[PDB]
Length: 62
Length: 52
Image 1 (cartoon, rainbow over the protein chains, first blue to last red):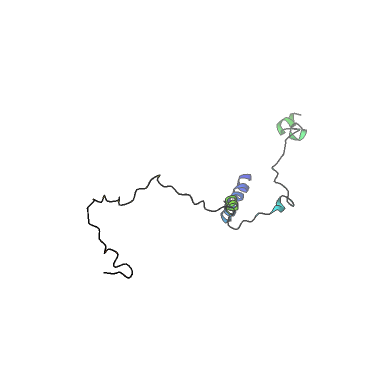
Image 2: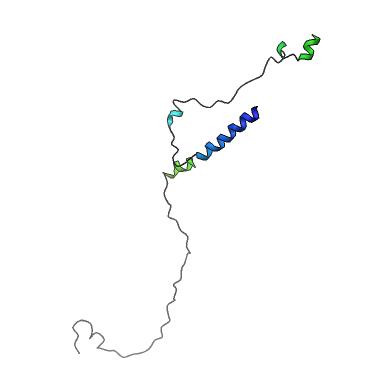
């Protein structure tokens, strides 16, 4: 699923980049003033041994 | 390209060239031989209103 979702995401970005025009691209200071800075994902996995993570086989033995 | 386009506005050609320390003429001066000739008081007769 993820692969397919990403592939189509990659494909249309490969097209968007094609349309990029350095000659017309204008820069504004409102990005530094009115628009938040890019933030990469900061997900950290924890509590890996909750009962809900217990595999079915062991659950039955339990 | 966007960055270079932004700084390109603040630039202009720096007219610099490269040549040799010494450039001799195409044709060097010809050594003229000395020949004796008498004083001639008529060589200015055609300059201005001359008198023959």
